[PDB]
Amino acid sequence: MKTQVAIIGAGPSGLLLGQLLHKAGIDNVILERTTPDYVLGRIRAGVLEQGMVDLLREAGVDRRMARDGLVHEGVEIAFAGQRRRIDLKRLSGGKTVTVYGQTEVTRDLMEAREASGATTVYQAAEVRLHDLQGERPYVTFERDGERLRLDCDYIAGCDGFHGISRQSIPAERLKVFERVYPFGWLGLLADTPPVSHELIYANHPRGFALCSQRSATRSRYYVQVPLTEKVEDWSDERFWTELKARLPAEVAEKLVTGPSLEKSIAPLRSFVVEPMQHGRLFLAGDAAHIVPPTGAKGLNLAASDVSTLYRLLLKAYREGRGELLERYSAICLRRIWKAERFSWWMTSVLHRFPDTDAFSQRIQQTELEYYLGSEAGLATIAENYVGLPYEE
Amino acid sequence: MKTQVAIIGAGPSGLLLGQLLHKAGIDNVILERTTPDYVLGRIRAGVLEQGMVDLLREAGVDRRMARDGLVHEGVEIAFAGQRRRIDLKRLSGGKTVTVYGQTEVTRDLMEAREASGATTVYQAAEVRLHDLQGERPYVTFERDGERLRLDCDYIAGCDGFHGISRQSIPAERLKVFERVYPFGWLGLLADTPPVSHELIYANHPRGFALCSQRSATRSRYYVQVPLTEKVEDWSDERFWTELKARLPAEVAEKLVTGPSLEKSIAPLRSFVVEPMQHGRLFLAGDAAHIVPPTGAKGLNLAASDVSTLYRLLLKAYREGRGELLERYSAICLRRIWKAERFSWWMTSVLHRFPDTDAFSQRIQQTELEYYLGSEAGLATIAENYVGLPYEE
Ligand SMILES: Cc1cc2nc3c(=O)[nH]c(=O)nc-3n(C[C@H](O)[C@H](O)[C@H](O)COP(=O)(O)OP(=O)(O)OC[C@H]3O[C@@H](n4cnc5c(N)ncnc54)[C@H](O)[C@@H]3O)c2cc1C
Ligand SMILES: Cc1cc2nc3c(=O)[nH]c(=O)nc-3n(C[C@H](O)[C@H](O)[C@H](O)COP(=O)(O)OP(=O)(O)OC[C@H]3O[C@@H](n4cnc5c(N)ncnc54)[C@H](O)[C@@H]3O)c2cc1C
């Protein structure tokens, strides 16, 4: 079989890239290691930037989002007995963020692809990339015991952190930057009304806590835990008690608790690889970089990578301007590094780090006091939170 | 579940390590991504060093090998109209090599493990390593939809070039050395009597050819092909004609051809990673390094890595000398680099390289003439071919 653009991974990155391209008349095939069900079981993201929202509208998959999504105009940070609200809309110049789960975005994209008739091969086992530096690269994979070959012009590696794409580039050609945090996030999804109409990020001595949501009757809560914890050691009962302990009393007493639909621990890390392409292979999303969930940038950076790749592929196919693809990494890395710096900053001021001396604790507290009390400080959080502008 | 040593991959490396350890009283669990059948379908190696042979005897899996294996005392190199034999036995000081297929070695090891009652989990999907730098590392995997956790003290990554082990070590902690050759080997396994009682490595203007065997009625032939070739473009008919064209007439006319049992193309590469361990994780075999098949060192280097790891694990468990494990990489890398240099040398003097000027062609030919005509030159090939001594 042959196609123009072969896409590895049917998560939001690949599906969004594949929708945009198909819409523009560029044939693409998506190869996914697992099943649609497995993909749909990942809870993950809840916060989307305006740029992600417009990209979904452009891809023609925004009906359900425009209806069910919640537009948020502010967020709250609670520390040292105080609760400070950041007016994102006012401080960022009218920009806002949208709360719509990643499961929903994925489901909408999967349905739009299903209907369009575009090719999608699930349970594509043992995917291997070949002739990346040639003019005719190809992908081999196993479907029901038989190994097929897919010929293409370009390959978009949208296979996540553990995908085959990044591994297929000669190690000596990549420079990795990584930071692993000494804690993870224990998340709990419940069918209960959220405790606030906006998100509450909390720095507490016992550790970080976050009050999020998915809709008016579905909440998502998180608490910072050491990497040595096991999810089975955390009953719903234990989670609620711990969460309550980390929140302001007035917030904790208004909390409607209930049994969990999902519970899991996500470890935290920062990771960037440079460059993000090799020959005819271009990395996008988690395949190229990871940001701690604190700044809500992962899925959103996946979106800007995809918007950039799509627009460069359009010029190549439509305008015969293939030389432009060489600019992929430079354009993306600029936005990636700034979003990494913000996610790193948020993570450092909101979490409890092991082995912290007196001076550092005081500086962490002072960072919050200064940034949340200065009009200029608030603006730096707001513009970064809503999302820095996409480069052209 | 808990065990002492968790082993990733049931190829010869993991099975051999697991047999040795079990025999010494150290419990180990082997996790394999595929099925026993898939493992048994890989043809691969045919030449074993004396050190590999003694290691199999020590592991108590040499009955069938001692019976069916063919001990070779010499090899032949054909170039420029000449056929020169290297008397390995005489030039290396009595050492020889043994021809016994890797499929057989694997089958013998699998049966010995089956009988011993030692744990082996096939179709162990989505294997992930955790807490490598801790005192209690663990492995998570999926077996029939359910994700299990395996606790252990040490983890031996014997999962090959594309395994999860090497990928689990922080990229910034490893320094990769790699060379990819512009050609691959098209191999053909036939149920016919070999053309010679010894192997024939041939440098011919059309490219490299190799006459090997598995037994008195089963041969293995190879011809050098560009990376752009597809196995389906090579009929048995086309292979035999090409092979015949690359061999000395007297050899080519004695050739008994026949339909193929197996046909495949293996690309050539040199690859070394330094160090070969991280915390409680130790890499072995193809997971740590790849050598072009020309010098017949891959499986053999896997054996010395395993012999070293086993002996260091024995001191740790039996003698409480865990500090010795830190020496793993230094000991192995010494043997690896020398076997890499030899495999690289063999590859460069026996193959046709694209874009070679007149001077280089003459030097390649002169290398053969000198090394095959000097008693000292012959000895350097012989001692390296039989295998350099294992370090203690
Ligand atoms: C707890 C948590 C909270 C988060 N919150 C936010 C938030 O509020 N906002 C935000 O922007 N980000 C957030 N993120 C991040 C976001 O979820 C990820 O960045 C996003 O899922 C990345 O999408 P991707 O398409 O790049 O890959 P992924 O979602 O990982 O999907 C990659 C796909 O490729 C497939 N694949 C892997 N290997 C292969 C192979 N060899 N062959 C074929 N297919 C393969 C995988 O099965 C998978 O389907 C959060 C993440 C977590 C963990
Ligand atoms: C054409 C050719 C000829 C050769 N000739 C010779 C010869 O004559 N002599 C010689 O010494 N060498 C030779 N070699 C090399 C030799 O075959 C390899 O070095 C040897 O197979 C390495 O063994 P290993 O156990 O390290 O791995 P492998 O044989 O690759 O096995 C690794 C195992 O790990 C499994 N695995 C992979 N990923 C995972 C995962 N995520 N989870 C669990 N399991 C996983 C794989 O399924 C596989 O079963 C030759 C190779 C080739 C290709």
Image: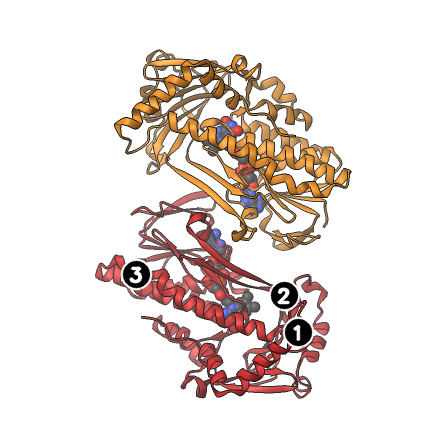
Chain colours: A red, B orange
Residue A36 as seen in the image, left or right of residue A209:
left
Q: Are marks 3 and 2 on the same chain?
A: yes
Q: Residue at x 59, y 31 (%)?
A: B303
Give the labeled residue for mark 3: A313
Name the N-terminal-most of marks 2 and 1.
2
Which circle, 3 or 2, is nearer the viewer?
2
Name above or below for residue A232 compared with residue B46.
Answer: below
Chain ID, mark 1: A
Q: Quadrant of residue A49?
A: bottom left
Q: Chain of mark 3?
A: A
User: Which of pointers 1 and 3 indicates the residue nearer the eye?
Assistant: 1
Q: Residue furthest front?
A: A359
Would residue A366 be visible to someone looking at this image?
yes
Looking at the rendered structure, whether the residues under marks 2 and 1 are on a common chain is answered as: yes
Residue A115 visible in the current orientation: no
Q: Residue at x 64, y 26 (%)?
A: B56
Write down the residue under mark 1.
A207
